Amino acid sequence: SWNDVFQYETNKVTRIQSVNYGTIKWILHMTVFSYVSFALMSDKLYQRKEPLISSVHTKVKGVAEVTENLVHGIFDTADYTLPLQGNSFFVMTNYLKSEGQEQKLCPEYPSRGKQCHSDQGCIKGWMDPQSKGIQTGRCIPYDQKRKTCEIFAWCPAEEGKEAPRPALLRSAENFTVLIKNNIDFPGHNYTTRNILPGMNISCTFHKTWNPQCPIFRLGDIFQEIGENFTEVAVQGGIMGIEIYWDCNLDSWSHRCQPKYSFRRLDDKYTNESLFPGYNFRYAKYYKENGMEKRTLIKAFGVRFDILVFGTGGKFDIIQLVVYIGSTLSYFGLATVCIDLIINTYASTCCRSRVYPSCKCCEPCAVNEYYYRKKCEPIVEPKPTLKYVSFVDEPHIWMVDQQLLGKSLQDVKGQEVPRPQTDFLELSRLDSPDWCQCGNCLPSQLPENRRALEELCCRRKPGQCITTSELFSKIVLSREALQLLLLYQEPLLALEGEAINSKLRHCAYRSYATWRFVSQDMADFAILPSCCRWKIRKEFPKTQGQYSGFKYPY
Amino acid sequence: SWNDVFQYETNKVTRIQSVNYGTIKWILHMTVFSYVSFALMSDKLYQRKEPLISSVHTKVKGVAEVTENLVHGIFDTADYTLPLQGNSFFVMTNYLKSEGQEQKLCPEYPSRGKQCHSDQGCIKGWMDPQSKGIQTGRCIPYDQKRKTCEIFAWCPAEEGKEAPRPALLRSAENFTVLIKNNIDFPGHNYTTRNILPGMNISCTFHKTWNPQCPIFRLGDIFQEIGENFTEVAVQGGIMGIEIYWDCNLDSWSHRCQPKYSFRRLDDKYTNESLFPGYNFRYAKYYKENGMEKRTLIKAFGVRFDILVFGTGGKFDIIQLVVYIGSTLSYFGLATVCIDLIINTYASTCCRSRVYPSCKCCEPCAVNEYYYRKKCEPIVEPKPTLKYVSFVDEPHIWMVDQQLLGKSLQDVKGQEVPRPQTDFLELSRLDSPDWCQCGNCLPSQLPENRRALEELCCRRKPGQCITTSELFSKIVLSREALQLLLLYQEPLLALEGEAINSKLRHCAYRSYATWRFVSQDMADFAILPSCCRWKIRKEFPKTQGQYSGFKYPY
Amino acid sequence: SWNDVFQYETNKVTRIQSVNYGTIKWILHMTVFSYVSFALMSDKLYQRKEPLISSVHTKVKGVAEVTENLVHGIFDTADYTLPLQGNSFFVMTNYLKSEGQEQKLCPEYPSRGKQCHSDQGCIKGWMDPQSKGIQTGRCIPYDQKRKTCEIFAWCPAEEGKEAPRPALLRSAENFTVLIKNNIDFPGHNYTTRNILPGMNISCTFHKTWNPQCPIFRLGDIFQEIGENFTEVAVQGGIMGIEIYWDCNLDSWSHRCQPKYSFRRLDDKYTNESLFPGYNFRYAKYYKENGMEKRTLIKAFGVRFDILVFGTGGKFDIIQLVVYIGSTLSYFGLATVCIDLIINTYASTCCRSRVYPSCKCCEPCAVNEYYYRKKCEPIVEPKPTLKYVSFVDEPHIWMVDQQLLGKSLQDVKGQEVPRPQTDFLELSRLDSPDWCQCGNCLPSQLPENRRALEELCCRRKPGQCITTSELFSKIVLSREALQLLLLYQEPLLALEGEAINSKLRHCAYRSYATWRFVSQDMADFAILPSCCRWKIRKEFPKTQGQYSGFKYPY
Ligand SMILES: O=S(=O)(O)c1ccc(Nc2ccc(C(c3ccc(Nc4ccc(S(=O)(=O)O)cc4)cc3)c3ccc(Nc4ccc(S(=O)(=O)O)cc4)cc3)cc2)cc1
Ligand SMILES: O=S(=O)(O)c1ccc(Nc2ccc(C(c3ccc(Nc4ccc(S(=O)(=O)O)cc4)cc3)c3ccc(Nc4ccc(S(=O)(=O)O)cc4)cc3)cc2)cc1
Ligand SMILES: O=S(=O)(O)c1ccc(Nc2ccc(C(c3ccc(Nc4ccc(S(=O)(=O)O)cc4)cc3)c3ccc(Nc4ccc(S(=O)(=O)O)cc4)cc3)cc2)cc1
Ligand SMILES: Nc1nc2c(ncn2[C@@H]2O[C@H](COP(=O)(O)OP(=O)(O)O)[C@@H](O)[C@H]2O)c(=O)[nH]1
Ligand SMILES: Nc1nc2c(ncn2[C@@H]2O[C@H](COP(=O)(O)OP(=O)(O)O)[C@@H](O)[C@H]2O)c(=O)[nH]1
Ligand SMILES: Nc1nc2c(ncn2[C@@H]2O[C@H](COP(=O)(O)OP(=O)(O)O)[C@@H](O)[C@H]2O)c(=O)[nH]1
Ligand SMILES: *[C@@H]1O[C@H](CO)[C@@H](O)[C@H](O)[C@H]1NC(C)=O
Ligand SMILES: *[C@@H]1O[C@H](CO)[C@@H](O)[C@H](O)[C@H]1NC(C)=O
Ligand SMILES: *[C@@H]1O[C@H](CO)[C@@H](O)[C@H](O)[C@H]1NC(C)=O
Ligand SMILES: *[C@@H]1O[C@H](CO)[C@@H](O)[C@H](O)[C@H]1NC(C)=O
Ligand SMILES: *[C@@H]1O[C@H](CO)[C@@H](O)[C@H](O)[C@H]1NC(C)=O
Ligand SMILES: *[C@@H]1O[C@H](CO)[C@@H](O)[C@H](O)[C@H]1NC(C)=O
Ligand SMILES: *[C@@H]1O[C@H](CO)[C@@H](O)[C@H](O)[C@H]1NC(C)=O
Ligand SMILES: *[C@@H]1O[C@H](CO)[C@@H](O)[C@H](O)[C@H]1NC(C)=O
Ligand SMILES: *[C@@H]1O[C@H](CO)[C@@H](O)[C@H](O)[C@H]1NC(C)=O
Ligand SMILES: *[C@@H]1O[C@H](CO)[C@@H](O)[C@H](O)[C@H]1NC(C)=O
Ligand SMILES: [Zn+2]
Ligand SMILES: [Zn+2]
Ligand SMILES: [Zn+2]
Ligand SMILES: [Zn+2]
Ligand SMILES: [Zn+2]
Ligand SMILES: [Zn+2]
């Protein structure tokens, strides 16, 4: 089967020289091409994108002078507050220091209504989880009007004390942080950094003037997003410094720069029971005067979380191939649309309701010509298929249903048009109850299938089709049938009953071709009893029943 | 070439009114549509998904009362153990404290068999990397039966001492951690948090009852995954609190909630040489009695790593377009399947082996009618192409191969069927060694290509095709040929040898059309010597050799 | 419309038994299949890939003996330097210690030219942001030739002092770090770790010998990437330990192993004003002799950032379906290419310029036969469409344009070939100024549209087509026209003016079919005045004007 391999199939097509259809086709093609190209370029769907891996190294620089009372102290954001310099860092903005605490008995701080109306109110032997002090069951006069429960704990106890207002280290808004960010795209084998040779050092970040300076003033960070540093400093907070890397690693469009943005990460309206702000407690234990003491510091501040995210794209051929394959089927849109137009306007419904109503749609009736040049309807050749023609009608009846002992003459079928004959070929030129022509005869077939041949040439009384001279010229012309037989077999022998059978079949074939036109219908046609029996009379059989119609398949 | 632009191509098609094929087509279309729709909806392939950036802020709350001996102490997880409150946090569950250590000489702890069988066993001047103590070469009687090597180091040395069992801070399983998680999808410009207004505060996380409370009891964290906190507390561990954000940012299906899950991250069965658990050593140096001392604490505990991951989807038109384009080609499945059925059942092999064996497959022989209505086979018109017809055979022979001095009569070729003639058109109606008809003549062509015309009308002896009256009516009927010529050229001049050549060509064309049927074969047909020379005799040439068959292309 | 549902469309095709085209088709199909398969397998486009979530637990092991002067001390990387063991860790490689500092007056260190040329140079009451010391306005003689400004600060002040060279803790290159890495793919529900049972413990990482040992010597880490640990130790740095997980979670191809790589993350050539290296300052405050003192340590070292990244793939049916759908349209490449070849080589331009120039391209002229068997050109049947035939020419003229009072005879039109007549069907066989035949008559139509019928049988003077006997046999043969009418309607009545109209129309139809061939052109043909008026004379009308050509649609 070598020839089976070497076959090539190509579809049969129909050019149409239509201005409208060609214009529509090209418009739709340009539209699809424009959109797919735009999507590819905008979304960079030709690039295989990779996420980055990041390293952050921060350096906070600030000295705050505090007058605590009176002692003038300096708070350097180099050793006092910054042992961690990386993704996240903390800048202290307030503190509550309790110097020289001794484990002894003292009143508890009156926080959130922590007081007593009577001595018996306090519970002996139970330590409050907030004050973290063991109650002795007595109530001390903490203040003149703010007496609180007696407790044995570190004293003077300050647990529950509110953060000082205004914040002690407000000057922290004047501090600066230098962020060094190293990224890599391991798949693309590309690494870069946010500081490059030839960058200003005295610069400070501004979203317009200095959008690439990695030195940030904290107050500016807060102002850029409408946050009040003075208020946030009191209880603390969490702020995000987002670094976005939208990086194009293609040589012809290379661009890998960071974009800095800011976002408050703590909730401003956190409920008082969910620990608003940001703080931590750390203690330093020291023995003074032979008595173990402890210095406790509750520090409030802003934790800055540096969030680095982004992707790096580089041209990938496989991605482009996949995208093109995905978008290729969209170029059949023109075909789909124009074929749908042809099919819709080829209907007989439009000439009856649409065009009469709208006369601007009349010239869209050429779709009927475009649809006959495009489609060839055919029917399933099932055994029950039969075609019927009546000389008193202009069209043909297809009886695909079975005859339940009912004469074929009395069967509705379904009307179909007679095919237009090839004019070029022709340019070279007592009776039964179901019979209206009077020339039909009872069928000799077995009673069960006798109704197939119970057909007449016409539906109303009149002259039989056999009376026409064309019937004799075509169907009963022994000369013409012999010529057709010789055309099929030039050396045919004109002797015996074989020739009489060959001529009878040719007469049937001739009537069916003459009155059904297409071979598709001529194959399943049914001859009337009149024509059938005239043919048989003029081409008899030596002996035996005529088989009648036999299923072609 | 404006008309070239305005062309529209549409494929020629063939409707088939088949219940089976239409049903199959629609079933396959519904199947493909259902699957593509289901995939789109389930996988959300219309959504452009983005990973999140996260910030975590934790607050551990717990006081553990320890009776160390006797002194009753409190271990507050606010200052003693928690200066870091973010992605990861540590809860101490055990400790080994060595108070008031002095750099002097003392025995080494007997850990992992660290002992001596003799004084000379110990190495002088060498410091063990485990005990971290410089050996003096002597062995001290550390214990009555556990003497160990003498060392100069911090003393009393406790290096290698096992973690106390049961864990001192078992009460840490009753501690609670509040996790505040802020996420953002920077591309989608969406941010949310795990705590929202109107949430219960007294709640504690339960996977069913309170699946959204971000307050977790550590013992519950361990119980939920079948881990024993009491055992893990002895040597420590690492536990993961996974926060999954499967977030849909579309308005009509908006859902962005966290799902909390837990996973032990350290290996339970870590080898003793790979440092099982989690611990760290930290020292506090202080001068006591004028002698520099050091307090060493080895802390065992559980490090909790909060792992936040997830994606946020939002409708993207480009993604939907790409998905639809990818899935469009699957709607040709019905076409592929039904065309394959037609092709397979159109074979002549099925009527010979399949249908006789299986009679339920007989009604699938209409595929032969569907395949003749669908396909038009053609052959490459190469110069070696020739077609041959023998009046004693019912079919035709295509000789695509070359004649190597061998008469065309004696060439196998390959059998092809004679086309069915258009019955509608016809309804209007001494000898050489290779000659079996006796009426053929030697070819006058040059010897090299003389074998082309060495053909007879039949393969077996018999009457020549020329003897039929149809040959004279069609081929030798000067009247008919003149009528055909006039049809082609109405004003043709019937004079000179030009008319005699025009008639000879028409006679050849007529024989070829009559005996090959299709113009495709009639073009490459080969006339027998008998017919050829009868035609030439009745349409002679004034002078010169007859050219013979000439390649149409 | 049940039959409307049960329709199946199949395209009409044309097999071609061509070795070249079949070979090209199969080559292109194999090429496309090979590439799509290769892309699928290489890129694993059948796998839905997921990023990992990671946990890292490190254990650094090293003791460095330092001789500070003389006191011999040990620096253990277990308690002195490592409280953090996770994603990032710090190994100290150098330090500057200032023991027993007292807040008093002293000279400032001469760093970066920090000196005075005169006492008045120093500013009173202003504290330098670098030295962090309040100036008293005087200049102390710090050194014999390096006098610096007087300042009140912690003393002896060492701010700005350069890091010692060579680094004190060079022995840190001999330290080892054990990295335990736990990953998970939450979607795939897969977790693994970098240490598995049966792994060597005494091993140390080597890229070839021990590529999976998670124990790393720091000096080896630096040597592997061409970094000098001795130099980096002086000022410090940041090094990355990248752990890549390319993990295949499919059972038949399961592989999930880590690949370790190293990358310096700090910039080697950082500007001196951008704080090169890595360091931090931490202080320990202690009261000595009743005077508050502070010990300051500036530590230089290398921060190691463990960067874990990777994806885990597992077979997904939806991904495979999407990929196949995307790549399906590429299998029409053979069709596109071969159809383009057929179209290009079917042009009449190739036979005139290409083949004469290049004779190796002659056998590609069969594409003209392949293109006539494949395409059926048609024209839009618009009202202005007209076809014209002149008996003195071999081809046909299509006049699609309007006649602006200009005789149709004098219209250029555009030449088209006359269709090849179905030879099988035929094998069964005083004057106006615009008239060249002399037998045409003035048109009786209204003057506005009178020019349509102003056509002659020929373009040059000569005999009229009507003079041919074929005109009388075909067009004026009342017998033949009656036979055609009877063929259409066998029981037609031959009486009245109706028959005379039926015959006149048939004569028009016969001329148009005889001289235009295709019904497409015969429909829009235009008869000459000579033939038209001869037909009308021999088939007159009782009374009334002849309507003339009427638009078929
Ligand atoms: O992302 S997150 O994870 O959330 C995250 C988490 C944390 C950070 N950064 C960060 C950096 C430093 C500290 C820290 C600290 C301490 C003091 C100040 N300022 C100060 C105030 C007043 C005075 S005063 O007026 O002169 O007094 C002097 C100085 C600023 C910061 C800190 C240090 C030590 C400890 N604990 C400890 C426990 C036991 C022992 S021991 O001795 O027993 O061994 C010793 C120490 C706790 C905190 C905390 C967080 C960033 C991100
Ligand atoms: O993700 S990871 O990266 O893996 C990661 C890593 C770490 C964490 N959290 C975390 C939080 C705190 C500590 C820490 C600590 C200390 C003590 C207790 N409890 C305690 C026990 C007994 C007694 S007692 O009985 O009363 O005695 C009292 C208290 C709990 C925790 C800690 C603090 C300081 C140091 N070092 C240091 C070095 C030099 C100097 S200096 O003075 O020389 O300057 C001062 C201090 C080390 C550890 C460690 C880790 C989370 C995640
Ligand atoms: O990714 S990143 O975020 O960038 C990142 C960030 C950090 C890390 N690791 C890391 C680990 C430890 C330290 C640390 C430290 C201290 C000392 C040595 N060696 C040493 C030298 C000389 C001598 S000597 O010669 O014997 O003297 C003895 C020992 C090594 C490391 C450190 C400890 C404490 C503090 N601060 C503090 C503040 C207030 C108070 S308080 O008392 O006031 O409460 C107490 C303490 C700061 C640093 C720093 C970073 C990894 C990654
Ligand atoms: N289309 C069509 N074909 C028919 C009809 N009647 C007979 N035939 C065909 O013509 C042949 C004639 O068979 P027939 O002469 O009746 O039986 P016979 O005596 O054995 O030759 C059969 O093989 C049928 O296929 C008819 O009414 N319509
Ligand atoms: N198909 C076919 N065509 C033929 C055959 N012989 C001749 N022809 C064609 O008919 C024409 C007749 O040429 P011929 O009369 O032999 O040469 P002439 O004397 O120059 O006219 C040639 O152009 C051929 O194309 C034949 O055997 N088969
Ligand atoms: N193709 C073509 N058709 C024509 C021409 N002239 C007339 N016809 C057609 O033939 C029919 C003859 O109409 P005609 O006899 O002139 O008008 P009548 O007197 O009303 O019958 C019309 O319906 C036209 O469709 C012509 O020149 N070319
Ligand atoms: C920040 O600095 C400016 C200029 O030095 C000063 O005017 C302002 O008061 C400072 N802010 C704080 C909060 O100290
Ligand atoms: C910010 O907060 C402070 C105190 O918290 C307040 O005095 C001030 O009005 C607020 N707004 C601005 C713009 O400073
Ligand atoms: C805080 O929560 C309590 C209940 O725990 C509720 O009564 C109160 O209204 C809440 N306040 C805010 C500001 O959310
Ligand atoms: C946890 O708390 C419950 C109730 O307060 C108590 O019964 C239990 O013993 C506690 N567990 C530990 C380990 O202390
Ligand atoms: C857990 O561990 C402890 C000691 O490690 C042991 O007594 C107990 O049986 C274990 N199981 C449970 C369920 O507590
Ligand atoms: C630990 O590793 C040692 C070898 O270093 C081996 O002999 C021993 O069996 C291992 N034990 C476990 C529990 O893995
Ligand atoms: C590292 O160890 C080797 C062998 O113990 C030694 O030769 C080398 O000097 C050491 N390096 C340093 C910097 O101490
Ligand atoms: C692997 O382990 C064996 C003992 O189990 C040890 O002898 C060998 O040295 C180890 N491999 C290396 C490279 O040290
Ligand atoms: C590394 O640096 C040291 C001092 O920084 C220098 O002596 C040495 O030549 C450098 N190169 C190597 C290979 O050690
Ligand atoms: C550092 O920056 C300064 C300007 O701030 C410039 O003058 C100097 O040349 C730079 N040096 C290097 C090594 O980049
Ligand atoms: Zn009848
Ligand atoms: Zn009848
Ligand atoms: Zn012969
Ligand atoms: Zn012969
Ligand atoms: Zn004329
Ligand atoms: Zn004329």
Image (cartoon, coloured by chain):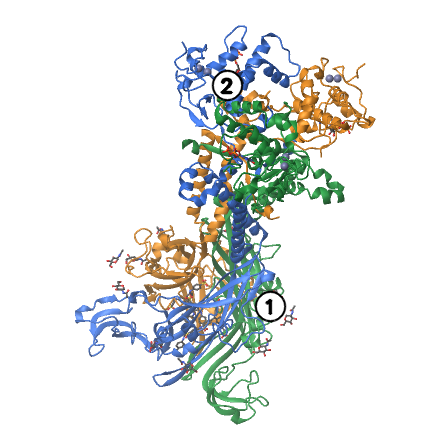
Chain colours: A green, B blue, C orange
Q: CA distance from mark 1 to mark 2?
A: 97 Å
Image quadrant of residue C220?
bottom left
Q: Amino acid at mark 1?
A: Phe
Give the image quarter of residue C86: bottom left
Kindly identify the residue that appears in the image at 59 percent across and 52 percent down.
Answer: B317
Percent x, y of residue C381: 69, 33
Q: Residue pushed farthest front?
A: A430
- Badge 2 sits on which subunit? B
Frontmost residue, B407 versus C428: C428
For label 1, the residue is: A229
Q: Is mark 1 within 8 Å of ligand 8?
A: yes
Mark on residue B551?
2
Secondary structure type for disc 1: helix
Residue C464, percent across and down? 72, 15
A346 relative position to B426: left or right: right
Q: Nearer the viewer, mark 1 or mark 2?
A: 2
